[PDB]
Image 1 (cartoon, chains in turn cyan, green):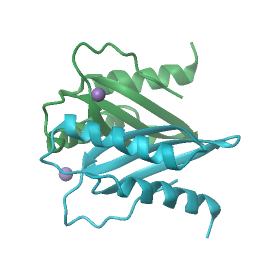
Image 2: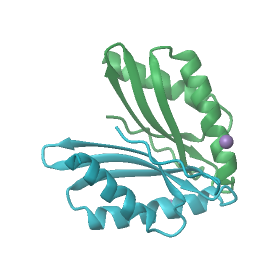
Image 3: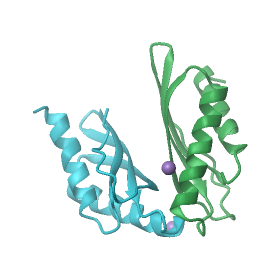
Image 4: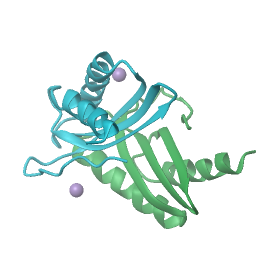
Length: 92
Length: 92
Ligand SMILES: [Mn+2]
Ligand SMILES: [Mn+2]
């Protein structure tokens, strides 16, 4: 429950379907009227290049924005996630 | 002018003194009472590994939080910045 949790879960689930995303580390989303502005950090393979992380972020942004129309702006950026890492996304 | 712009500029200037930071791509900062909560994306060498980007983010977080005491929480994450890129940081 919480419609905002459901929206945040949609964002996370869309992002986690994009190849190269190991998980979503952090998501902050807020309304400006009907539109959402959001900042998301995705976890990526540590051995990737930063150029590769960059292309994954761009793919995440395209996929999320294409699926969640009320999102007017989404910044996607990257950090290392090791593969033994089950840390659930942090929100708020 | 704008005391919030000055705080944001302090954050950017502290971060840009950390080795490996090519620039600050994006900064979002808000007050909860007297404390600041902030999300920052730093630009990093594209040929770096994501593990290296990660260690730069961690160094940025330590340096910024150590210099700006009112910051209670700072998420630092990374993206590619090419070196011909003079793009000024985006705020708000
Ligand atoms: Mn690019
Ligand atoms: Mn680490």
